[PDB]
Image (tube, rainbow, N blue to C red; front, top):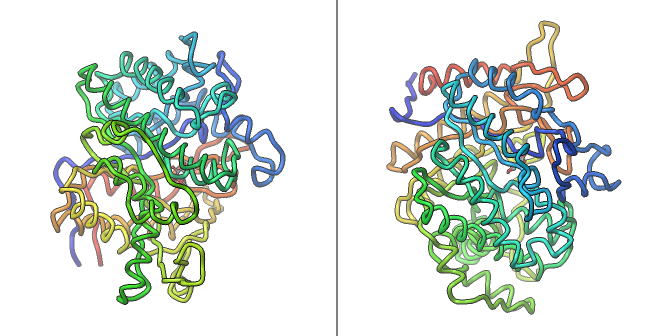
Length: 451
Ligand SMILES: OC[C@H]1O[C@@H](O)[C@H](O)[C@@H](O)[C@@H]1O
């Protein structure tokens, strides 16, 4: 037996996103977002599910905060719905939308919970999409004007700020694969969108500094460790390319002020040679108080000479792993290896785990309990590896469990449950899962026992 104890001031949190939990999609003057439009189009979401009602958090936030206080989370990461603030993306401010998040933040503080705000978690106002969306560079200024309203109203009571959540998913799934809003399918557009997402991050950070906000700001990137299939140089180079086309396409601009050259080479080979102003990468790499990342699984990559990419997943390795209800492999060591790479490659930054969690099939037993043993095991195993990285010198400051509530899992709808709290989407009843009660004790004890 060994006792696992995290650092004295370690921040234990849980995370949600506005569109995934709030509902009230057309109430109090809120403007239509691209995810309203995407969800209302048949064939885009599993089972025709929508985020129209979701968890109805807009009306039940007081119950959800009381649940947060029972579990004892020290920080709550949520996102603000831009179209609740500016229904047209710019123009007239909707005070009613503002007052919602002002109230929500105030009750969180009154309940001893530290708020942590994501400014952009994919709900772009549809009016801005009608003018090109993130393909239009003007949208990066509209985002900064919206951030200024939030910074002015909440900046000096919210200690932790995330500009963007997973720009790489917005780019890849929303603008190349087209399976996320706004449903666009064009490689060049998705790369222009990637740049403008990053540029809006840099503009918001610059504004954050110029407003002298007494808080910390960062960005939340989707990151995984990409393992080479072997120690042969061809597989290492293949995994390096895979990473630079995924999370490192955003990591390197943010922390080093340059796109990865090996990924640029590939896009040039495909016929796409990118050209952005010199100062754009300066702006993108504004110093940030921490780097934050969402991690769930790991990749395993092999050299694939006859393919266009030059690499492919090492399926013979991947089939040895257990999988979650999402079909993702479970490999806890991948979180240690990822944390150690962040610490090694980027000058030992302060690091925040803005999301970690797992989806499993949930069952409400005859006792009313949800005995989600596999979810507990996932979290405990991944947290053990995060603790290991801390012992080896990584400046990991916070851990946000995805998610507080079962919610709208984008194109999967309500078919995938990530919560430590079960939500019945027909009755809106909340039931804390056994994983929620486990986390409650982890927080109280600042860790757990390993047998
Ligand atoms: O797949 C589960 C989660 O993926 C995350 O990386 C996204 O930020 C969440 O919005 C989503 O619910």
